[PDB]
Length: 85
Length: 85
Image (tube, rainbow over all chains, first blue to last red; front, side, top):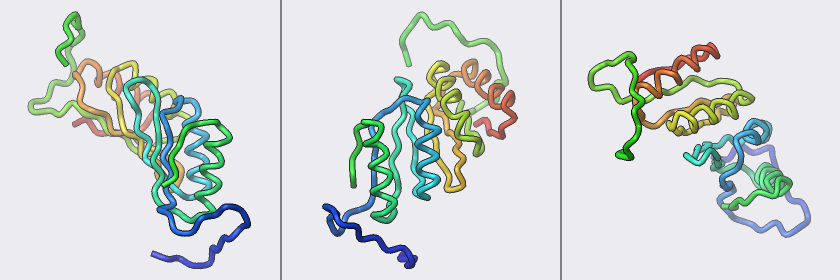
């Protein structure tokens, strides 16, 4: 539901109405602790599926645009492939 | 699966109708890279659920008891809680 308080409306190409979800591509297990830290810090939480190849990817459950933006921008810092949903 | 040349099935806690699954309790994110390696090495593979508190746990996919036995003892080496299915 809507928890209020947090409002975000920064100038940029910030499109209205999305799912506010981010899915990543399979990345190396050693980056996992730090990305979990981001999700925890951004209070997003995600399910990290380990693939048999020895890589994992997370799917982050819906949050706000402000938390969303920072999380995807993080994956962008890592140069990882991701999906904004 | 049926891949042949795999003689690795040393005795373990052989309980009837076991699922051969091990789920852990919420543990620290920095140990996640190591445990993901263990799963990948022990050919188990798992889903790591991150909690909002900043801890994660894995649910491992069914494997042989000889593989999982070492994995559960690994969790014990770490002093983490787990369940053997």
